[PDB]
Length: 185
Length: 51
Image 1 (cartoon, each protein chain N blue to C red):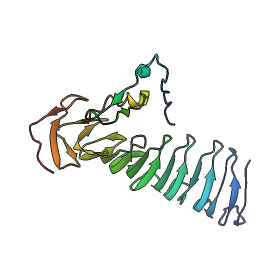
Image 2: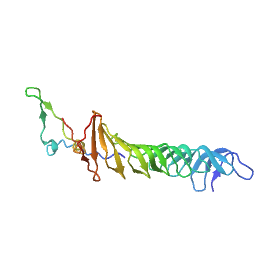
Image 3: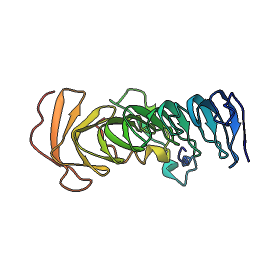
Image 4: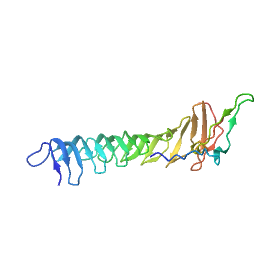
């Protein structure tokens, strides 16, 4: 048995705002529709995870922030089906993804920062793995090719901040074969 | 979750057995080259850059 505060109907349908504790032990804050939740509020889990958001129809919704048990965090928009669009996620090892989202997996155009190296990936995503029409950004290198699961593939090219452009062919999984084209810019 | 850094070996039984002095043209003063760290070998082996 939990407990609750805020205004309510004589039936028991809450329609106010306040703190609350649920039967399964965890506490939260937020507003209320007649028998449902909304408003900014804040959720607190037993494991230390937290959520602030719109809470539409008692579902994860709207612009907000979620702090997961493993120390990773999110800020961005959510919807009922774990959807979608612009947002940012920060990983346990200080890496950061910023871009489109879908059903809790990375999807569409987006950016991933490799905080250990400082380089970035910028490209299309589907269901978490990498895809082509993409761009890695190193300190002096830019590929500018195609990707498949995790590694580059296909007729890509390495662009440099010297005034050079090197084409290539990732024929194997992690080996490049080069062409004679080294044209400027 | 940063990785564990592997410490350098200042002892003479490692990569730093021999000190190295580098000079650009003879007669110029010799530059005391730094010591080796394993981070400075790997993943530094993977890069390959002109001097």
